[PDB]
Each structure stands twice: as structure tokens, then as C-alpha cells.
Image (spheres, coloured by chain):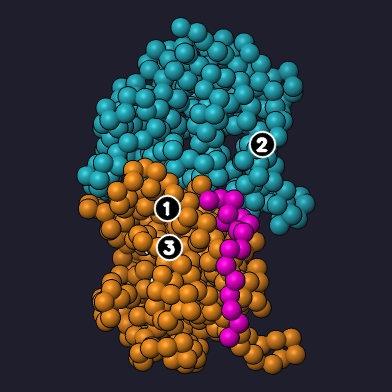
Chain colours: A orange, B cyan
Amino acid sequence: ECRVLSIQSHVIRGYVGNRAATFPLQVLGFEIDAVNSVQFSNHTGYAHWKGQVLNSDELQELYEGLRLNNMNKYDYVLTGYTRDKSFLAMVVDIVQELKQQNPRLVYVCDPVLGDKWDGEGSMYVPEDLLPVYKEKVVPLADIITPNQFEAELLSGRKIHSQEEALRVMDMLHSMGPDTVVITSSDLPSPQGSNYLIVLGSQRRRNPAGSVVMERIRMDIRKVDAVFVGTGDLFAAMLLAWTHKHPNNLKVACEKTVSTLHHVLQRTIQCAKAQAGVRPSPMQLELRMVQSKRDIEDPEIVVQATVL
Amino acid sequence: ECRVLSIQSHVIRGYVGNRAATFPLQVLGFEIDAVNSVQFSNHTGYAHWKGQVLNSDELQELYEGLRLNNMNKYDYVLTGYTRDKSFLAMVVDIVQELKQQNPRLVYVCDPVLGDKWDGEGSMYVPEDLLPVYKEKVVPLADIITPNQFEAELLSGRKIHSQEEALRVMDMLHSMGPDTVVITSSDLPSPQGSNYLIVLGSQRRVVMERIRMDIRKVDAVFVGTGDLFAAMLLAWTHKHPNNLKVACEKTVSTLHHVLQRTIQCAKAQAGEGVRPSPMQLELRMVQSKRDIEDPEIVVQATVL
Ligand SMILES: Cn1c(=O)c2[nH]cnc2n(C)c1=O
Ligand SMILES: Cn1c(=O)c2[nH]cnc2n(C)c1=O
Ligand code: NA
Ligand code: NA
């Protein structure tokens, strides 16, 4: 089996965090264990929400149970939105130990920090997490999925073009991860302003022992709606597809993105049908269960360009 | 869509409570929402375990979030192992309101209280819960899945035979639930000493009673009851007026999961060697196909 330790948020209603990542990965045959970092009624995008949060001591306690039972052996660790520094610090110590047990362990990290909605975006998490991500998390990460804003904060350099983005990706590689994917863009696109850019870069040592790097690009059609959990789903699927195609970033990224496409298209349709009228957050909840078939064998609806 | 609110335990490693009921129900297309009554590193059958418990106040606030957003509309509610009196009490108040919100809501309840090994009965929860189950839970439930021991405790009458079991089930029906299934019993089967009898009764007035003779296994699995209730919910949903088929698919599904689980357990633990709780964890993920369309391997007989 292939074991994944996913430490993310949980909601009763809806799909974000572990709710967005668990079903798909289970459907794909992964033994995914879910540590819920928070338990809320629904995501914070709704008008109302209530719930509890897990603290760093409780996380450590849970890991103790696993350790005591000699069940602290994983192939992958997967994290995303993290709200607290001591929690993030604990996540770091846990990954560090799991990597000692298994040096081949792959840590997939979605470095959630914030986004843009003008020019100079804003953060979604305490600023004191940035230094921890820079000095502790990223260095341990093997695969990261920052958006442009996050790539800039992590690298400490702004991005105004594709070449600058690639330079940032090289900087991020030097910080630690062999696979870097700047998930969202807003860089010029030959197809217009209705498209966003996805850039991916993967460094690996081939059979002959040569260290090479593969770079790809995708121009994805934007959507006129605010979805939640897509980044969590993107990271989970990237994990799954790079696992299946370890030396082919292109195919891995094309399947990840296509899976997202099918889920979002189905979600958009159902959302509209449930009215007209801008759908509510509830109606825009990802149609995960209904996308089982697309998750298993996604029809490739987009092709990446080689860089 | 068919929404299900499942209030059960959560474990990081393994499959029990919500871990045993969610994946299968999702695979089957249900929009199941999971309220984790606890979050443990693994079930209590291991040498060690750590975790936290959700208290009744936390359950209420989580529900408040749903209510405030008008997301308190469910087609089903699913509960199982509960340990606190106050938590269970909070659970009935919620089902109470959810039923007020949706009169057609079906409440599937697995009355976890205890079980009888050799002959004597052992309790799994504080006895201060029995009164709550009898007086408030069961009366609210529409489908219950007690083993023989639990049925005896709920009805207050002992069972020594099949017809006494059916009379107890008639008693449980009068208490409220239209569907009653005795998932496990000490009753004898002509199939041999290695089989146990399962009895089901559904009211809809017409009554449908069925019987299944199931093979036993010299191994202790955790989460099977949780999975049984989830699947019974799923299949009774697909076949609402046919307890016979709903139970054959439910039991057939468990068979495939346990069969696969036992084989992998022995493969990991050499022949002759008794598998550990870790090796005995249900092989849920690998049973996706069996959950979607279970090959029928057991026939129920209409009584
Ligand atoms: C996007 N998103 C959310 O909106 C959210 N809300 C609560 N947890 C959450 N998590 C983990 C998340 O990733
Ligand atoms: C059988 N069983 C257990 O033994 C257990 N232990 C902790 N949660 C548990 N749940 C939800 C359960 O169903
Ligand atoms: Na992101
Ligand atoms: Na039981």
C-alpha cells in the first residue's frame, strides 16, 4: 500500500481541506490517514460558521499514539492551510521524524499564505508563519504548489513575467523541493485575459545518474465564481498523479488539471441549475462524490506546452 | 441529492466509526457529512491510543453553524458507538429538530451497548446510557441494528430461540423503528456450528421478516458493525420495500471486505500466526468495487 498522512481542516458540510483531498485519494487507492486540524460546520466563506481547532499539543499527542503503536511509517505527508505557528512548527517536527523512518518519504506542501485581488494581495494566515515556511517547511518539502503571490513571498522576489517566474521556481528548488508548481498566475496569455497560467518545474536524477529538469506550462480558462477547496484538491491530485508518473511532470500536471476541470464543470452546471442568480457558497460546493469516475480516469482536456 | 449526517468516531489510522462509514457511502453516491465525535490515533483495540473527545457543547455549536446557514436538512442521520449520556442526549435533540425540519428523515441507529462472547454479557458503555436509548433514542430511530445482547437489553426480554427473537423485534417495533435487524446472535444454524443467524423485520400494515445463516470467522474485526449500518442504510435506500435484497447486498458487501481483509492479514502474518489488530484493519480502499456492486454470496429466506 501507499500511505499518506494528510494534516488539514475538516468541515461537516462541504469540501475543503481533508474533505477535498480524502475521497479522491481513497478512490485512487491510497491509504490516506486524515488528521483534522480543525472541525468546522462549513468553510469560512459562508455567512456563518462555528467549530473547534486542534492545537499543537493535541497534534503531538495524536502522533504519539501512532508512534507508540509503531504506525509512524508513511510514504507521503500532505499539508495545506495552516493557521498557527506552533502548529506549523509541530507539523515540521513530525515530518522530520517521519523522514527519518522513511528517507524516501515525499512531503507534498501547499504553502497557503494568501493571494491577490488588485495588484499587491493580502495574507490569509498570520505573518509569523512566513519565516517558518521559508526556513523550516519548504526546506523539508519535496513538492510545493504556491500561487504567484506565495511564490513571491517565499522567494522574496516579485514576478512580472514567465522568465521571472521560472527564475523564482529555480530559487524555490534551491530552497528544497524538486517539484515546484506555481498553481495560479495572471501573467500574459496568448489566449487572452480569460486565461490563467500554470507553470511547473521538476528536477530529478535519471537512471544514468544525470540531474535534469523538466518545465511545463498550461493556459487554463478562468471561471466567474469563487470556489473553495480547489487548491486542496489540486495538491492531492498532483500527489496522486506524480506518484503514478514520477518522471513525467507533463502528464502528471495534465491529469491533475483535467480532473479539476471535470469537477469544476460539473460543479458549475449543478450550481447554476440550483437557481440561475449567482450561486451561493453552498451551491458552489465541489461536486466531489459525483465526480468519482472523472477522478479515476480523467479525460485529458488540456495539453501542457513544453518549456 | 441524498444527504446523510453521520455522528461517529474518527481515527487517523484504521477504519471504525466514520472512517468505516464515510468512504463506502461516498462511493455509493451519498452526500455524507461526518461529525467526528472523537479523533483518536487508532481504535481502542490496540496496545496504545491517544486522542480527544467532542463534548456535547461542541456538538451543539457545530450544529448551530449548519442551522444558521440553513444546511440542517438531511434525508438520513446515522449514529453508532456513543459513550456519554450528555452527548447522546444532545444527539436526540438534534435528530428531533432535523425531523421537525424534514418529517421524512430516516434515522439509522446502531445501539452500541455491548455483546456476549462465550455466554455471559459484557457491556461496552456506562449503564447510565441504557435508559436514554430505551426512552429517547430508540423511540426516535427508524432503523436499528442491535446484536442479540443489545436487543435483549432494549426489550428487557431474553432470547433463546428464533421465535423469541422475532417477538423481541416486534417489541422494538412498537417502541418506534419500522426496521429492525439482529446483526448477530447465539442462535444455531443447520449449516453447522460455524454459522450464526441474522434476523430482519420491516414494517410498512404489512410485515416482512427474513433470515440469513452466516459463516463465522476466528478473528476479531473492528468497525464491521459501523460498516453494516452504513451499507444497510445505502441498500434499504435503493430497495425501500425489499428487506430481503437490502440485507443480501449489505451482508455480501461485508463478506467481500472481510474476506479480502483476512487474506491480507494472514499474508502479512505467516500461516498459523494470529494476525495483529493492525493487520486486521478492514481493507476498505481496496474494496471499492465490492461496495459499488457486491456479488451476492448469501440468500435471505422470507419467514
Ligand atoms: C480553502 N480552505 C478553507 O476555506 C477552509 N476553511 C476552513 N478550513 C479551510 N481550509 C483548510 C482550506 O484550505
Ligand atoms: C467498534 N468501534 C470501536 O471499537 C471504537 N473505538 C473507538 N471508536 C470506535 N467506534 C466508532 C466503533 O464503532
Ligand atoms: Na493556493
Ligand atoms: Na454492535
Alpha carbons under labels 3 and 2: distance apart: 32 Å
Measure the alpha-carbon separation of dots 1 and 3. Answer: 13 Å
Under circle 2, the secondary element is loop
Q: Residue furthest right?
A: B271
| Mark 3 neighbour density, 10 Å: few (under 14) some (14–19) many (20 or more) | some
Q: Nearer the viewer, mark 3 or mark 2?
A: 3
Where is ligand 3, by quadrant?
Answer: bottom left
Q: A162 above or below B279?
A: below
Q: Quadrant of the rendered structure where residue A93 is?
A: bottom left
Is A305 left or right of A146, judged from the image as shown?
A: right
Q: Which residue is mark 3?
A: A230
Q: Nearer the viewer, mark 1 or mark 3?
A: 1
| Residue A51 vertical position relative to residue B110 in the rendered view, above or below | below
The residues colored magenta run: A291-307
User: What amino acid type is highlighted by mark number 2?
Assistant: Pro
Q: What residue appears at the point 55 percent right and 40 percent down from the top-left corner?
A: B28
B22 or B2: which is nearer to us? Answer: B2
Q: Label 1: which residue?
A: A268
Q: Position of residue B74 (x, y in %)?
A: 36, 35
Q: Do the residues indicated by labels 1 and 3 lie within the same chain of the protein?
A: yes
* Depth order, front residue of A218/A131: A218
Which element carries disc 1, helix, strand or loop? Answer: helix
Q: Quadrant of the N terminus of chain A?
A: bottom right
Can you identify the residue that label 2 sits on? B294
**Mark 1 surroundings: few (<14), some (14-19) or many (≥20) residues within 10 A:** many
**For the residue labelled by badge 3, is the local secondary structure a helix, a strand or a loop?**
helix
Amino acid marked by disc 1: Ile
- Residue A7 visible in this rendered orientation of the protein: no
